Length: 239
Length: 239
Ligand SMILES: Nc1ncnc2c1ncn2[C@@H]1O[C@H](CSCC[C@H](N)C(=O)O)[C@@H](O)[C@H]1O
Ligand SMILES: Nc1ncnc2c1ncn2[C@@H]1O[C@H](CSCC[C@H](N)C(=O)O)[C@@H](O)[C@H]1O
Image (cartoon, rainbow over all chains, first blue to last red):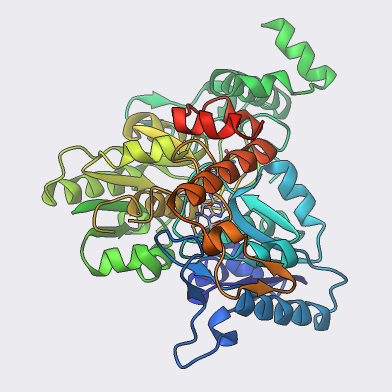
């Protein structure tokens, strides 16, 4: 029962992944658990402020360390009571390591994650220094909040958990091949005949050549780092 | 009034960005409009089918998406949009980044196609899709989260949505650490430059932090940065 806790000002945003699709069916079947913790539930004052003006001047607001520390402690206690051995705290940040398939595969082995979602101009650095084990970025772009990155990370993990993908792009270092389904003819374009109903073996051959050629056309640096089985090497030299 | 149309089996997911945060305030203020089109409203009610050649999973059918995309196109024309590309979210697309995001701001609006399951029929892409974009080298269970990532990244750079000049990747460097109250957190002080500094030495410190952080974490990005003479002077004043 993989345990996910997200520290977020907008818990309702996570309904996008707990209430729909394959990730929703996983939450509803209790294969995973998603608990949302709002730092405003650990803030002081009638307004429950979690943000304040940055030292050194500058626009915007910075999330205060003290409510987030309390929210992370609560999340740590929730995970311990859930039977988890250890759950690392991940901060979503453009300054973290870049999520890719290799990272996803490692995350699948974890008992669970606590994911910290920032807002405003970001989170006080001392909070990161003391409470965060890992920083991950979903890409070289800036979003208005860490909730969507958290959801991207969570979704990428949930779909590889047992009882929730062998042909995934990047799983073998190559891109997936073009897919075709009914109708037989679409706006003058037909399915390649090899795929239509030939035997099991020759369809598999075509799929590899398509993965390699597509990977070659779009992402040639991945061809540099790919390792081929002997059956695949045979197919290439034939062309 | 930028126009967004998303083709998605799960329109409710997009509440995550239209109802919360800065992107939500933009939708409520009518600075942007997001319209969801469900391919199930255009089927004869199946929208996915088994792939030719066998293989696991389902492939989204071209004909409902063609009808949905055309409806999206007429929706966009009736909104007055001149230039609206059809974008398909796919890990086989070009990788989104901040430079790409800036280019999207130039469009009158977007039609974004969200695939599910094993993906979208290849021929539908060939005939109806102008651009393919990936948010990263990992596989998600659907294109809705990537669509939202793209939309959020665009929305936060639109006029009337101050504090975006200091973003990561804006100048090719990562952002510097942020601090706010209290003066001391669990033994850690705010750097004194930020506490009691002034315009020149704070600006110097922030730049040296951006540079050093980029060098430690993303050393390839230093290759692609061009420095003002004042920044070049600041660096040499250290080394
Ligand atoms: N590409 C991305 N990957 C992961 N988290 C991201 C992200 N873009 C924004 N976020 C998170 O969204 C929140 C608000 S944006 C703050 C951005 C920060 N000044 C910077 O450029 O480093 C932060 O917690 C930030 O880490
Ligand atoms: N990194 C990413 N960027 C953009 N769209 C993505 C994505 N990961 C998944 N999607 C979209 O999510 C949907 C279901 S995932 C299908 C993935 C496909 N087998 C492949 O390996 O290429 C598809 O429409 C896909 O384009």
